[PDB]
Image (cartoon, rainbow, N blue to C red):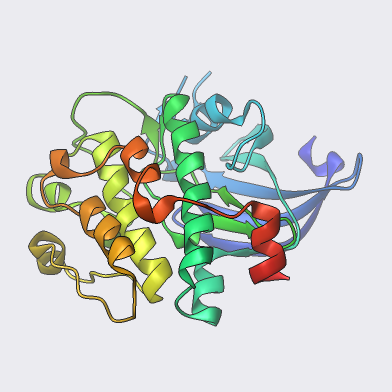
Length: 269
C-alpha cells in the first residue's frame, strides 16, 4: 500500500521517463521522489518482469554513491511506481547552469569529477546510464554533492556493440548518428565531453547531426587550454581515440579537485 506509507507532494516534472512527484515517507518523514511509469510506455523489461530501470537501480543502489538510490518499488495494474531517494535542498544541473551561465573551471572540475565517480560506480556495477546530461544531474546545494538520476534509457553494460539508443540525441556520438552502432564506455565518454563543454561554456556544443559528425568544437567562452584539450579528447571522432575514465581523471585539468563541502562553501552557499 504505497498510498499509505508515502505522502505525495507536487509534481517535480514529467516526460519520457514518466511522472515524478515530491514526497515524504510517512514512516520517518524521509523526503523521497515518487516516479510513475505506465506499463504501455516501457520497451525494456528486466528480470518477475519489471522495467529495466528497476534492475539497473538495484545493481547500483547498494552502498553510498553519487547516484540516486531506489528505496522501494510497487507494481500497479497499469503502471510501476518507484520510490527514490530525494536530497534537499536541490536544483538540477540544467537549471543551475541556466541561472548562472558558464561555470568557473574550479566549480566545473568539482562537478565533473563527481559525475565521473558516479559513472565509474555504475560501470563498476555492470550498468550503463546512456543519458548522461545536465538534466539528469541533481545538485545537493548544502553538501555540494551531485547525484545521477533517470536510468530509464540505460542497459546492462556489455563489451559488444549496441544497436539501440533512446537517450538524448545532441548528447549521442557520431558513430550512433552515422551507423546506429556504438560501444558503451566510449559513447559515455563522448556524452561526458558534451557535458563538460556545457558546464564551461553555458550551453552544449552541437545542435544538428551535421555538427556532431563534423566534430569541430568552437569555444564561445574563455576556457583554459587544458580544459579545451580534455574536451576535444572526449569528443574525438574515432571512438577508440577517446580517453578511458582513468585517463580523464589523470588529466592535467582534473588535478586538485575541491571536496564537495568546500565546493558548496565557496560556490553554492
